[PDB]
Length: 83
Length: 365
Length: 83
Image 1 (cartoon, rainbow over the protein chains, first blue to last red):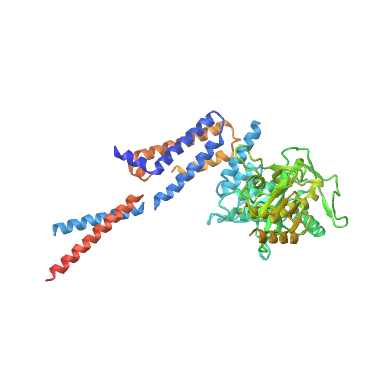
Image 2 (image 1 turned 90 degrees about the vertical axis):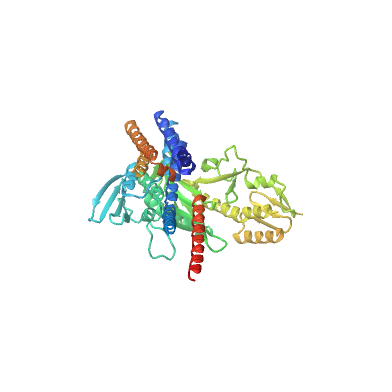
């Protein structure tokens, strides 16, 4: 149950959320064959924000290195424990 | 109003997301302007995209291995082959091609689209008026008109990878600063507007229409003021130029109280305590960005530029110095008087304006 | 992949609105398809949604403090056992 709470905590989740909302507005506009510029510009800037957050996620690897050094920590602890 | 709104939305979408520089996006852009386009394989490593219209042919060489544009060539089907599509840089032996630069130096197609829209305008509206010839020669006629009128302005073609006739002044550091850009624009207001060829005659020292039979319809010669940008905006007396010649009036839309900073400076008591400011303007100040200088209005270029230069050197500096926290300072449309100490007017030389500002700064500091 | 397809379809929308309503409707349906698969792919994977900032610093601090206390106790053991 806490998983979804953690997922909602990171910004890019909200980013995909309002990106979906903006495309929903755009499709509603084109359904009414009345394309509103503000919806499209909101869509493009939200997409750009998505893409910058896509870069920001990548520099990931730090957590992975922390994970391997954590495994090193507990394996050293177990070794010294059996010692 | 639906078509005008749709065209305005299409222009907005074209400007807001110009697309990435790819062969497919360049082809789609050319097709969106009604240009005929074909792709040829010159080699296993090189493809050419050739695009054509009535007069213009543009070859774009694409390196398939590098994912990059290698070359761009413009060819005219006019009897005039001398159209300058290179940037005018003083002291570089390599004339840098505007079209190639717009596809290699920029992150997007916006620079290329603007330059292509300009070439397409000349193509569509050239017939017996050849606008490629006339626009090239016009830069020489304006340069001569300034020499004959003793105007200290430099004329350059094609500045910063953009088509246009650029009018430059010497700035305080001897650096050239653009004052205005002259170019052709579609006349949205009157498709029947006759645009004639005007030549500057060395003999008469005037603009002359040699061939009243040589006209194009639905085009205007536009003078755009290049703001270095609210304090860097140029303001004109409302009666300085006929309202029919004003293409773009910056309407301060009715929800932000930006008077000219000049008029707010007649209303706001936050002055240098040494100066009593007196307003002697008879007219309202309006912000004008674009002028129609077509036909008989080519004489106005020198008057508009003198005002723009006087406004930058005198008015804007007087305002900057008065606005930084008793002598009477009278400010009018064409003259400024500091009590009995110093005066300058719009018809004085630039050297008189500089001396007035130096003396004014020494008193206000 | 949905990102480049979204980009491209976005651009032929903004380049050619003068296409007949058939193409506009079909292309908007295509974008709705791509974002539908986008939201699905977001949905099944918890790890990405977690990916989708001081905690990393706190983990680094705890790792370095446990490392230094391990080094100190090992130095003490080395000093004591050599007798």
